[PDB]
Amino acid sequence: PQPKVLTPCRKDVLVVTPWLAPIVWEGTFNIDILNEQFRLQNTTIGLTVFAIKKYVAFLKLFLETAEKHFMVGHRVHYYVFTDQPAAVPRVTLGTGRQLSVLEVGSMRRMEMISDFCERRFLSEVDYLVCVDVDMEFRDHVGVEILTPLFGTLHPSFYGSSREAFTYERRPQSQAYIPKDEGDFYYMGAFFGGSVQEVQRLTRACHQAMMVDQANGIEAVWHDESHLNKYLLRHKPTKVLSPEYLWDQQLLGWPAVLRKLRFTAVP
């Protein structure tokens, strides 16, 4: 369908940031075009997930639903970090898709990605997508999200003013953002980018959390607080709308959300 310069497809929402990054909503992208572009590069996406203690119970649905909706037709590498490798369910995967189980014994999430697993990610995947396991895919999540660096609009704050944002406000913490600065409030639970840029962000977030710790302070939303400082200083190249991180039980299904793609499990 021919793009019409004088008819916008979405008039109800901001679809581009003030630094000219796309904000990704249904109706802003032709998935066929995008797929071609990423297919021509034989793109591999890595999807990383922590499943610790009782959160391994979430893996089966997370995985099942990822096969249905996530990067379908592209190469995909799931990396599952767990304390119970035996509890990881065997889910049958589509062609070009694989899973690795990564055993571990707060801020170690950021540590694991940036330090321990650095060389591995660099050789195996082109992009990294970092999400929470207590979720399911309900609709398309695809290469429209891919870019050097993205975050996602936190769903209880997209419609709000910045003084309301739950940024860190104590200057003694590295994640400090003043009352009059800040573009959006990004969710700590869905971010990514190229491997290079994802390692930069998680290296920086670790380094900053080490400092707060050495000083007996802890940011009010922990890794999400440092994420928000990062993304203020280094602006994401795409921002995903709340279509990509929703909780239907707490917020319903507003008309402004034409699809709910990735949601909390009740």
Image: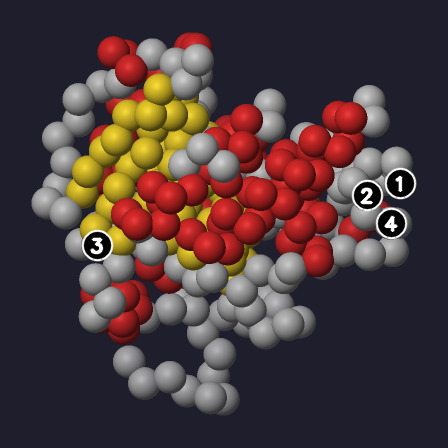
Mark 4 is surrounded, within 10 Å at the Cα level, by few (under 14), some (14 to 19) or many (20 or more) other residues, namely: few
Residue type marked 4: Pro
Give the total number of marks visible in the rendering: 4
Residue at 78% across / 26% down in the picture?
214
Residue 64 x %, y %: 23, 31
Q: Secondary structure at mark 2?
A: loop
Quarter of the figure with residue 18: bottom right
Question: Quick check: 1 above or below 52?
Answer: below
**Between 236 and 110, which is closer to the camera in this rendering?**
110
Work out how far the residue at label 1 is from the one at label 4, CA to CA, in angstroms. 8 Å
Residue at 40% across / 48% down in the picture?
128
Residue at 17% across / 22% down in the picture?
90
Q: Secondary structure at mark 4?
A: loop
Residue 233: tell me if it is visible: yes
Task: Report which residue position mark 1 lands on.
Answer: 171
Residue type marked 2: Tyr
Residue 174 x %, y %: 78, 40
Does the residue at mark 4 contact the one at mark 2 (Cβ under 8 Å)? yes
Residue 117 x %, y %: 41, 36
Task: Report which residue position mark 2 lands on.
Answer: 176
Task: Report which residue position mark 4 lands on.
Answer: 178
Question: Quick check: 122 above or below 31?
Answer: above
Quadrant containing the C terminus in the rendered view: top left
Left/right placement of residue 245 relative to residue 156 reads: left
Mark 1 or mark 4: which comes first in sequence?
1
Does the residue at mark 1 contact the one at mark 4 (Cβ under 8 Å)? no
